[PDB]
Length: 500
Ligand SMILES: Cc1cc2nc3c(=O)[nH]c(=O)nc-3n(C[C@H](O)[C@H](O)[C@H](O)COP(=O)(O)OP(=O)(O)OC[C@H]3O[C@@H](n4cnc5c(N)ncnc54)[C@H](O)[C@@H]3O)c2cc1C
Image 1 (cartoon, protein in one colour):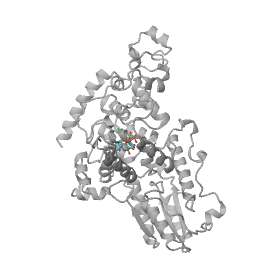
Image 2 (cartoon, helix red, strand yellow; image 1 turned 120 degrees about the vertical axis):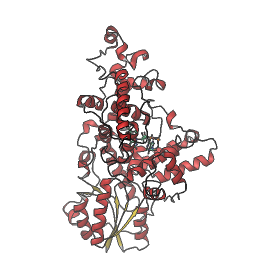
Image 3 (cartoon, helix red, strand yellow; image 1 turned 90 degrees about the vertical axis):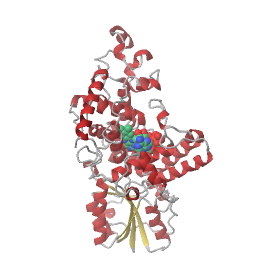
Image 4 (cartoon, helix red, strand yellow; image 1 turned 120 degrees about the horizontal axis):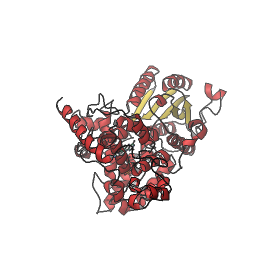
């Protein structure tokens, strides 16, 4: 006999998964011919390429478990193989007599190299590789080609292109495996019958003390549930305007599908389709960019630009990225990183992020502006690194693209609009409920100065039971000074970049 292998990296789902579907249709149209091994490889390699926080490990843990459960309903299971792909594939190709290897493609530079290295080994051992582009609605390679070789650097140009592009058909779940034996133990399974079993919380989350609330359980199952719940309110869906959603409401004002899209637990293609259906039905609806489909197109846009630039996540050697003399201030960085900037609004955001691993888009704006061009004049690369560690939805392309946007390094050039770490939150949370929740030391402060505790007299501070400098830090910088400085600095950097 011989093996068919689906390799999950992203695309952690059964729905709308051409790569997995193909393996399943194949084994069913030729029964008794083939063994099926859907695998995930727990690469030690990415830990050296990427920071991963406790919260994201738990989401991946929950994601793998859900995928196991899902595959067992199809008369299969998930095989979680430990080890580096370069070491793993030689072995299993031979040890499993692998005829076909499918996977969903991915544009991240680590993926690209790892995937080419595997496609080389697969050719050498006569293994048939078929790859699918189903992580994004559009193939960035087709977008780029339609634009004569370059990625469009504006949303609207991007939209122009993708509008004249074929929407792909969305698949359903694969047909249950008909009459499949469980693959016979291999060399590794024989010495340990649990060696390909889904990791437990304990194996994956080395730092259990860093886990915040379990709010967004990983996995396809929950992604589909959460999507169904979001689309319930068709008016909210149809009329959605991203800029008008609150960053600091206590419940998320957007869908929080981002972690599910990031891992491929939800197909972006299914989501786009379901949204299309609601828009046909609802004649009064918002349009890109502010619309919900618009949000998905942002995702497509950043994937397209990122696909064309291997150094997307760094300032140096990045065709898109303004060269800016960011400064090193390790103290300021640490204070920002841990929400001890002494700006409550910023602190609350940084604290929500560390605890829960998701914050609203405009909350990300606020903190990212503060760290970079707004206040601390720290490289967006540092911000990126902390987001990468803390966000459930951390996404190489999306994280880098937005950081470049926010720091006015790329795509956005109007650096003289600066968020106020004092005023910005006030528009949507005048009572400061959000701040009370995440910065509870300040909970006794009236709304009049909860955004601005340094406005309270020392004796009122004692009264509120939080004295600035002992219970809550003084501001690490004075917004009113530094932001004016940073505009000049930005102005200078823009000029020297203009003249190269
Ligand atoms: C500094 C910074 C860093 C960011 N890092 C990430 C990241 O690592 N991963 C991530 O998924 N998003 C990132 N974003 C984009 C955006 O903030 C999040 O996608 C959004 O907050 C996720 O919440 P949601 O799913 O409720 O979004 P919704 O408003 O419900 O949007 C639905 C989906 O559309 C996509 N989307 C929405 N906004 C954007 C956007 N600005 N760019 C690209 N796609 C978008 C996401 O997949 C999101 O799930 C970042 C934004 C900023 C400003």
